[PDB]
Image: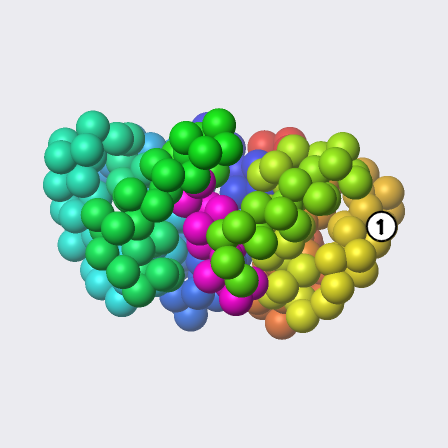
């Protein structure tokens, strides 16, 4: 029970994505988190997958649950599938094949594999090249693969070099005393909101009750 800064930022991003007020975004998210008994993050993510698919939230969930039972995955994983497949513009079976192809090939989570696939979409590169870049960062900065891919996409959303992205991220981790995760989040949210980092955070803090 409580809103970590992280959750708050995401919800901002959702509010943005839906194009609703952040009061209504958070109302919907907290309503979904209880109705489904998921994390708040997962509730926001579900809102964002439904939007991404151009569907209603029930419809998305109904579909996820047909993939949860059919493939024996977790709900979130089912949502990720749907999202990945959308992004690609393929079928779920194809998406699922490619992801379990990356999962085995690289020794990662299914979730990681999907996200790699989605990063590739955004970067406009091959999945081989995306993994390349992510492994380059992982090593260069001693960061996790997740971080690496995150940085990549954030660098993309900003329309800046990965170097400059890191600079600003690190600069926000020093200036504000956040983790790298948080900084990246903040950067992307602010870019999606079309505001400063300071504005985005102040907005996030209005929702933050827990201490991330």
- Secondary structure under tag 1 reads helix
Query: Camera-side residue: 124 or 184?
Result: 124
Q: Quadrant of the C terminus?
A: top right
Residue at 44% over, 51% down: 117
Residue 12 appears in view = yes
Residue behind mark 1: 171
Please identify the quarter of the rendering in which residue 189 is found: bottom right
Residue at 72% over, 44% down: 137
Residue 46 lies in magenta, yes or no? no
Counting from the top left corner in percent of width and height, residue 93 is at 21, 47
Residue at 20% over, 28% down: 72
Counting from the top left corner in percent of width and height, residue 173 is at 80, 43
| Vertical side of 141 occupied by 107: above or below | above
Residue at 48% over, 27% down: 107
Magenta residues, as a range?
Answer: 113-124
26 to the left or right of 186:
left
Counting from the top left corner in percent of width and height, residue 188 is at 62, 58
Number of numbered tags placed on the structure image: 1
Counting from the top left corner in percent of width and height, residue 133 is at 65, 50
| Vertical side of 61 occupied by 193: above or below | below
Please identify the quarter of the rendering in which residue 153 is found: bottom right
Please identify the quarter of the rendering in which residue 88 is found: bottom left
103 to the left or right of 85:
right
Q: Main secondary structure of the magenta part?
A: helix
Residue 200 appears in view = no
Query: Camera-side residue: 68 or 142?
Result: 142
Query: Camera-side residue: 154 or 29?
Result: 154
- Tell me which colouring the rendered structure shows: rainbow
Q: Residues within 10 Å of mark 1 (few under 14, many from 20)?
A: some
């Amino acid at each position: 029970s409580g809103v970590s800064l992280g959750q708050a930022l995401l919800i901002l991003s959702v509010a943005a994505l839906l194009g609703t007020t952040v009061e209504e975004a958070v109302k919907r998210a907290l309503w979904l988190k209880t109705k489904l008994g998921v994390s708040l993050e997962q509730a926001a993510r579900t809102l964002s997958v439904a939007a991404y698919l151009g569907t209603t939230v029930e419809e998305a969930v109904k579909r996820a649950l047909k993939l949860k039972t059919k493939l024996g995955v977790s709900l979130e994983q089912a949502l990720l599938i749907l999202f990945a497949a959308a992004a690609l513009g393929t079928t779920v079976e194809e998406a699922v094949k490619r992801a379990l192809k990356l999962k085995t090939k690289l020794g990662v989570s299914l979730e990681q594999a999907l996200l790699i696939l989605w990063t590739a979409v955004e970067l406009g590169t091959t999945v081989e090249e995306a993994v390349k870049r992510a492994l380059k960062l992982k090593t260069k900065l001693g960061v996790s693969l997740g971080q690496a891919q995150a940085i990549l996409v954030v660098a993309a959303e900003l329309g800046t070099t990965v170097e400059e992205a890191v600079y600003r991220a690190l600069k926000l981790k020093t200036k504000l005393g956040v983790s790298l995760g948080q900084a990246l989040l903040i950067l992307e949210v602010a870019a999606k909101l079309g505001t400063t980092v300071e504005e985005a955070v102040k907005r996030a803090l209005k929702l933050t009750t827990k201490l991330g």
